[PDB]
Length: 219
Length: 230
Image 1 (cartoon, rainbow over the protein chains, first blue to last red):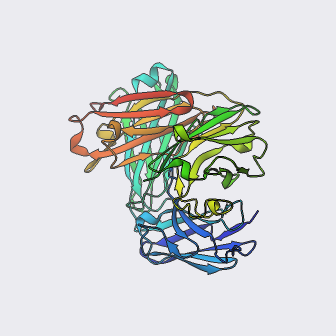
Image 2 (spheres, rainbow over the protein chains, first blue to last red):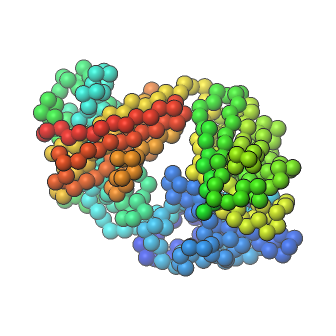
Image 3 (cartoon, chains in turn cyan, brown):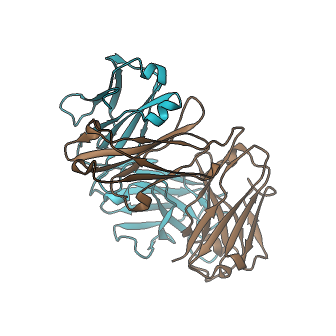
């Protein structure tokens, strides 16, 4: 099949600066009608691809003027004149010239924005979960930038290891921030043997590490 | 306003079959060639099959030819994908796809546009069991209050396979919602949280309900999230 190679695969861009994505094809995308069926798509997380450009350079209806396409033969370029927050996601070139239609691997556009300290929130386990014999304690770091953050769990001042998992959202399409969940999992027995549950957060935007904690039985 | 809605994604044991559906609306279905395309890390975006507007001709990708069947029922505005002899590498999100432009309604012009996509339906092929989630409140309190903001949520724990969806107050609350990517636990079951930020002052005046849907287990849970007085 036709192979499309995108470069780069990760494209960090400052808000308001231009972005350029390369798509190279294993063979000329000129079809026997003399036209070139090279499209560009926009995919947001949990969303389907959305076509932005068709036949190399034609903007779809409703697509902002900041998106443009060029190239010929085997070499194509998508340009974003000024990256806006809503431009975060993965961009794919697609060829329909030589069936089957094939896609490049995707280029992930990441926005570089100003430093934003996380808000830090902690949630005790529910009584409903404790009746099932397990305690999940959740720490939320909300709307921060950059992505790099350290979360440490302390139980009665004991640093925990190997009993928590983290998840990080994709970059927000409005404010270009990340959010992070950290879930500490204990048995009901271990949970009810200790008093103080604490989430300690380190981030560039914080002037010193932030602790959010609760005492079991107060909450 | 062409719209496509896929159904049927589930966990399938290796070697077994699954039929997907796509309900078409907002366009004259019988005037369009219709496709299936899937997406996974292993495959990237991969075209699978097309059926012509008149249903006479079908074409298939090498990887699925002889295992997958595309068909259409115009009276039901429905496209089908019968997937037989499923393999681990068929694990993917499956999309229904068509085009706005049917100028040249024959091979190969219906591969040119590919600009109408459904929402996708997830197919998991593994030797494992389907399990519906437990849904627990992440109760707001002083400990989930920071300046002008409070957080609350739902923990959607111990389900398989992906995915789950979470709405808040049946879609009345969308601002400040973050539904986290699922993480695979040591048990081989997924867990995620869905959180929403609200004004700090709002705690104790408002009802919050997370609406959780795990289509693969046919599980639906509405969970009321009430503050902890602490």
